[PDB]
Every structure is written in structure tokens, then in C-alpha cells.
Amino acid sequence: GNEVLRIVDSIHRDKSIDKEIVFEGVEQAILSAARKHFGEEEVIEVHIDRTSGQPMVKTNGREIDRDELGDILGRISAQTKQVMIQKIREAERDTLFDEYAQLRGQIVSGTVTRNEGSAITVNIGKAEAILPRSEMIPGESHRPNERIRAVVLEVKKMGPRVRVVLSRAHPDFVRRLLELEIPEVNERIIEIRSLAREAGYRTKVAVSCADSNIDPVGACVGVRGARIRNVGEELGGERIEVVRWNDSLQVLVPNAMQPSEVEDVILCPMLGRVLVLVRDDQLSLAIGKRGQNVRLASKLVGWDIDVMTREELDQQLDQAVVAYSQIPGVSEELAEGLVSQGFLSFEDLSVIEPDELMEMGSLTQEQADVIVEYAERESERIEKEQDLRRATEKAERQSQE
């Protein structure tokens, strides 16, 4: 009876975990002891009264004799010991899973305990969480016994301990921080529609407002744009661009292509690609340093952005027709049809939907597959031909001697 109360207090004082988890653990220990004795045939349930501590064990809804119940309670409480703790830790893991699994995408804070190159262990005080390399903001310094916060990436239960994976590199981290820093966002006045992030470098934010007379970007900017930079400094100097969200790609895409200016926006649904026309002087700015700009603009919009000028597009259309005409089974009319729909290289043709290629050229299943195989081969040959020329230009290292 009260022998159970002695145990639940002893573990609670030692292992430093609350009684309710311990009670559940002891119950599962009694239950397992009851399963082994009575067998798997009868349905078994166990309950321990919290106040008194007296175990209630039922088999198929029926109580069990005090005799056999005494054998069960003495087969557990007696040291043999760590098996019960395995049930208690299993209960703790189940509880911590329930709480943290609902917290996915949400900011959690803690202190750094151990730091290796591969991962960082953070103590949030209920349990130890790990921050892996992939989820880290590059070059950041996190030392033992220091305050740190991040978003919960995922929660899994594997061993008899709960695994909580964090991220400072996830887009959701920026989204949360913006909600905290900008009162218009946490008051729901301004909404964050879309987000595109390269962690530690640049993040594009598309926002909108229910009120049409309200400028959503200007609301986020505020006076000096200080609140936006505050989030950026928390990310280690990550650049944050806030733009205006729109349901039309004729609006949203030029907005996402900022600072660069856009002439024409062409939609190519079959390739899932938006073709953006940009003048020569704006070409470098449109792409970005390593191509960061368009890359982020693509994530933000949800399409594939291909930036070209008008002159090099006209050149691209002419060559694409001649190239596609080389393939037997591709008529000049069908070749022009592909180019008109946004297909330029052989890479684009190889990834075409067979069904769509059949309708456009009035082709059978066999004829469609054959064409695709040509595009695959030709794309592959073009790539290795470029590598050839690239390698033979590297053969000019003999210009030393």
C-alpha cells in the first residue's frame, strides 16, 4: 500500500522527475509483472491511487487475490530495480514527446552544454536537445553555459530517451523572430505569406494585409527599419528583404526579383518555369553573386525563374527550333510548338510530360518516349562536350613551360 509511496518519493527526490510520471512508470512495471504471471490471454489493467498508493490490478475487469497481488508487488519493489526505472524513463520520454511534438516550428530556449563540431547539445531544462551541423547558422559561436534559442525541427522517440532536434537554419526561425519583433505581425494585422531563406546570408519575406489601403511592407519597415535589422542581427548579420505578396505572378515575381527591374514576365506552365526578361545592365543584379537572388526569388514564388535578356532569348528561340528539328519524328511545326511553350534546351525536352508531348504533336506512346530518349542523349552529349572543351582548355597549363 504505502510501500509504493516510499518508492515514488525516492525516485522523485533522486532522479528529479515529477510524481505523476513516476506513478505511470510504476504502474507499467506492475502491469508487466502481471502480464508475465497471468499470461497474455486475459486483459490486464493497473491503477495506483495517488493519495493512498494502493495498486488496483484487474484481469478482464475482475480483481485479483491479495495473495497473488502480494507476490507481484514484492517481485517489483525488491531490488533485481533498474527495470522499473526503465519503465519510468519510458514514461518520461512518452510525456516529453507529447509536449514537444506539438512545438514543431516554434522557438524554444535553453543553455549550451556540450559543443562538438558535428552537433550542439542544448538544455531546455526538461530534456537535452541537439542541434546538428545542417541546422546551424554557419560560423556562429555557441559555448557551454550560454543562452541560445531555436525552433524545434522534429521530435522522435527511439531509445528510452526523447530526441529533440532544433534548427537555427530553418525558415520558420525567421518567421517566429519576425512575429516577436514586429507588433503588426503578432497582432495579426500583417501576415507572412511566403519565406525563402539562405541561413546566415539572405532571407526574402513576402507579406500582405487584409486591408487594401494598408501598405504591408511599410508596416514591417516602420520608421528606420530597425526591427527588421534586429532580427537580422540575431541571425548573425543575415540580410532580410521584405516585399509585397500578390496572388498574381505579374506582380509577385517582379517584387521578388528586387532590387533588379523586370521588363517581361512569361509563364511556362509545362516546365513549371517563369521566364523573366531583364536588360543587360540589370542582368548581373538579377542573378545575384552566386545566383542567390533568383534562387531565393524562386523559392518565394514557388516557380523556376529563368533570367535572360530579350536579344539572347530571340537567339535562343531560333537555335532551339533547329536543334529540335535534328531529332527524327520532330516536325518543324512541332519543334516550333515546343519552343513557343518555353522549351529551349534538350534538358527541357527530356523532362517533358509524355502525355503533353503526345497531344501537341499528335504522337503515340512509343513516338513520345523515343523523342524523350533523344533529348536525354543529346543533353548528356552536350554536357560531356562542354566538359571536353573545359578540360582541353585546362590542357593549356603547358603555357607555363
Image (cartoon, rainbow, N blue to C red):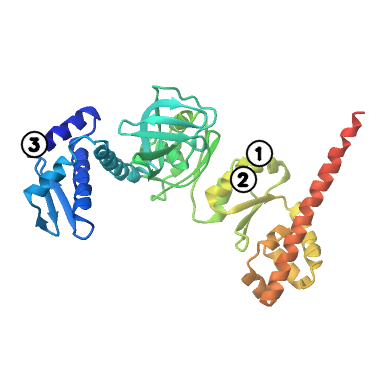
Q: Which residue is identified by label 3?
A: 2
Residue 396: x %, y % from top left: 88, 36
Q: Amino acid at mark 2?
A: Val
Label 1 sits on a secondary structure element that is loop
Residue 317 visible in the shown view: no
Residue 57 visible in the shown view: yes
- Mark 3–mark 1 Cα distance, whole angstroms, equals 70 Å
10 Å neighbourhood of mark 2: few (<14), some, or many (≥20)?
A: many
Left or right of 243 on screen, residue 7: left
Q: Which residue is identified by label 2?
A: 294
Left or right of 400 on screen, residue 61: left
Q: Quadrant of the C terminus?
A: top right
Label 3 sits on a secondary structure element that is loop
Residue placed most toward the observer, 361 or 222: 361
10 Å neighbourhood of mark 1: few (<14), some, or many (≥20)?
A: few
Say which of marks 1 and 2 sits in front. Answer: 1
Residue 268: x %, y % from top left: 62, 61
Q: Are marks 3 and 1 in contact (CB under 8 Å)?
A: no
Residue at image location 52% in from the left, 56% down from the top: 248
- Determine which of the numbered discs, if any, sits on residue 290 in the image: 1
Q: Amino acid at mark 1?
A: Arg
Q: Are marks 3 and 2 in contact (CB under 8 Å)?
A: no
Residue 368: x %, y % from top left: 69, 72
Mark with earlier residue (3, 2): 3
Q: Amino acid at mark 3?
A: Asn
- Mark 3–mark 2 Cα distance, whole angstroms, equals 69 Å
Residue at image location 65% in from the left, 42% down from the top: 291
